[PDB]
């Protein structure tokens, strides 16, 4: 038998396009005798189709309508062709989705309704990590540092009185740097909030961290975790598209700290399967949390892969391991 | 035209039976002129069926298999009969599910995908309220009092040294009192925890709060919220308990109960509705119990009782929740 694996991609998200790239990379790294892939692509209009494989513009490729069903008796997909339907039972879903509705908890809700095993984090962990201000809330409770931040929903005024520049303004729930601006003067503040609301009605205001931006790639369920090599940001497209150095030029102590911290958060946040912890390392040598990326970019240029690979885990290894982790109980 | 409102009930949850009762109540109260309902029962085994309506063993009568589709082009149901299928567009979904898969973000997950509007709390607040320990995390930040709690997952050893008795052991994510115990002695502790793991691998341990058990029903989107009369558990879970409405408390205790309940709903980003359970210590202070995101709606339920006391008919409550979904 092969394992029929469901590979979802695309999605009604600002990161749709990256998603396609990540799914395209996945597809080239599932070896021959093991998987029988089903490429479920969600269009930017939220339409579901089963296609020949991710890439562009696969919508214009051979495409059958179909959906992941929430019915357990199906434990898979319905294929919808002109009034007639078929059912394909999957063994496992791999949700290669970034951003809104993908790392939100949205698809992890439909999945849990399916009872089908899946890769990556929970509804909970996904919710906690997409709202950066809940992540900070959790990280603090585990004794982990975080920016100093304020939160502003549609109904609240911005607390300018209280602010010390420079400042980072961001949607509370976005990624790949959509909506993020760096304000330095009061007057440039309202516009920044505005831009950020194009992406979330709830807006985050952060007091700027000084330090090097470090990134750690985590894998595992529960307590048993491994990390990749620690990366470092060197020298509008978000971090994942940034020039990095691997491994980061930092103390061996610094490195373990960075890693232990990443795992400590991953654990506190209840993460599962994988995540990419983003961190700050100040000159005093102390560590601050940025973000927890629960289903990080997996593109040929993405950070997490680069990080696992440098630690001796091939892309096919990572997928192998994520797969077994998803079926782990 | 009537309003196509899909009414989902049942669910693969310990609270299945209570959801069917809640659906049966709602069903009596959507009057003849406005709604054209669609009763989507999810069986105890997780099968999805369109039936004649909630209650008894609905699973016995006339159910056609169908699912709510995550596909935005459909904006409703697909009906699966004989290898053939039809699509029914929905204006709105009312998810009358309680507990696991119904208050924990799973159903809203499918919903959020589908683009259809829906009654009640979103994925993020549903999750934050399902896990009682997360609820406390949030509440404390909002400057609201909670119990002294500890948490234990299968890997971790319960911290016997820290604890003080009495103490309460409970699934971190459950309701209707499934798996809740009041442990007396260290000896009886391990048994409870196993009791509660019948329901959730992460277990929650609380130091016992002392005071009147006070309930508050909330309604609204954003900051513009209203409340029912405050209820009090006259001294098989909470919802089924002997209660008194309104609670026999000071006018100021009352203003503070509502104010507190509303502030928590705000802080947790609740929407549509929620029932907030509280503790009123003899000192006049208030400590959080639980936020129930889509509480019992049965004839004997607390939320309904609280709202009709404030002059909102069960029909009035359905009507409001709906517009609130479409706002
Ligand atoms: N508080 C802060 N202090 C210093 N720099 C910040 C702060 N917040 C954001 N930044 C900077 O701007 C970027 C903001 O992206 P952040 O990770 O916060 O949100 P994001 O949308 O998840 O972006 P990404 O997914 O690409 O990491 C960071 O990479 C960092 O360069
Ligand atoms: N820390 C505590 N101190 C005192 N009593 C508690 C404590 N925790 C729980 N209880 C009591 O035991 C029951 C626990 O129910 P709790 O709200 O904790 O979980 P639940 O399963 O959601 O119950 P329900 O949804 O029916 O309210 C409550 O009725 C309350 O009386
Ligand atoms: Mg991100
Ligand atoms: Mg980042
Ligand atoms: Mg409950
Ligand atoms: Mg309660």
Image: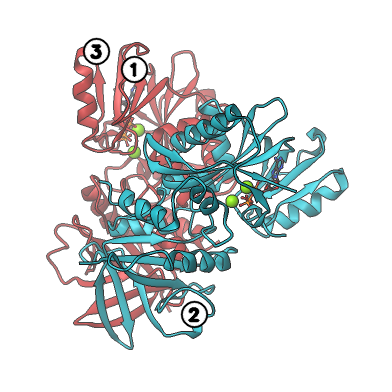
Chain colours: A cyan, B red
* Residue B159 badge: 1
How crowded pointer 3 is (Cα within 10 Å; few <14, some 14-19, many 20+) is rated as some
Q: Residue furthest bottom?
A: A82
Dot 1 falls on which chain? B
Instruction: Please name the residue shown 58% across and 36% down the image.
Output: A136
Determine the CA span between mark 2 and mark 3: 61 Å
Residue lying farthest to the left in this orientation: B60
Q: Nearer the viewer, mark 1 or mark 2?
A: 2
Identify the residue at horizontal 21%, vertical 21% (top origin): B190
* Callout 1 touching callout 2 (CB < 8 Å): no
For the point 50% across and 67% down, the residue is: A11
Q: Report the residue marked by disc 3.
A: B186
Residue B146: horizontal and vertical position, in percent? 46, 24
Residue A291 coordinates in the image, percent (x, y): 58, 43
Q: Are marks 2 and 3 in contact (CB under 8 Å)?
A: no
**Label 2 belongs to which residue?**
A58
- Marks 1 and 3 share the same chain: yes
Give the mark toward the camera: 1 or 3.
1
Alpha carbons under labels 1 and 3: distance apart: 11 Å
Q: Estimate the x, y position of residue B118 in percent, counting from the top left.
A: 45, 60
């Amino acid at each position: 038998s092969h394992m029929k694996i469901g590979i979802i991609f695309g999605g009604v998200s600002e990161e749709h396009d990256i998603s396609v790239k990540s799914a395209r990379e996945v597809a080239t790294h599932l070896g021959t005798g093991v998987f029988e892939p089903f490429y479920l692509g969600i269009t930017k209009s939220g339409a579901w189709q089963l296609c020949d494989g991710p890439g562009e513009n696969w919508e214009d490729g051979n495409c059958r309508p179909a959906v992941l069903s929430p019915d357990r008796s199906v434990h898979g997909l319905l294929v919808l062709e002109q009034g007639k339907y078929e059912t394909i039972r999957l063994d496992l879903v791999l949700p290669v989705l970034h951003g809104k509705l993908g790392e939100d908890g949205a698809i992890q809700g439909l999945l849990e309704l399916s009872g089908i095993p899946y890769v990556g984090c929970d509804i909970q962990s996904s919710a906690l990590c997409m709202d950066k201000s809940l992540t900070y809330l959790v990280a603090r409770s585990a004794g982990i540092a975080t920016p100093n931040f304020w939160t502003v929903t549609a109904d609240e005024k911005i607390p300018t009185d209280q602010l010390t520049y420079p400042v980072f303004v961001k949607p509370a729930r976005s990624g790949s740097s959509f909506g993020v601006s760096k304000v330095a003067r009061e007057e440039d503040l309202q516009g920044a909030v505005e831009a950020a609301r194009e992406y979330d009605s709830k807006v985050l205001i952060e007091e700027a961290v000084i330090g090097t931006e470090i990134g750690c790639a985590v894998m595992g369920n529960g307590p048993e975790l491994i990390t990749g090599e620690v990366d470092q940001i060197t020298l509008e497209s978000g971090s994942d598209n940034s020039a990095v150095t691997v491994p980061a030029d930092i103390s061996t102590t610094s490195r373990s700290l960075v890693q232990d911290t990443a795992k400590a958060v991953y654990r506190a946040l209840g993460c599962r399967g994988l995540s990419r912890v983003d961190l700050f390392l100040t000159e005093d040598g102390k560590v601050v949390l940025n973000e927890v990326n629960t289903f990080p970019g997996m593109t040929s240029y993405s950070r997490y892969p680069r990080m696992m690979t440098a630690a001796g885990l091939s892309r096919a290894d990572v997928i192998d391991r994520l797969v077994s982790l998803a079926l782990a109980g």
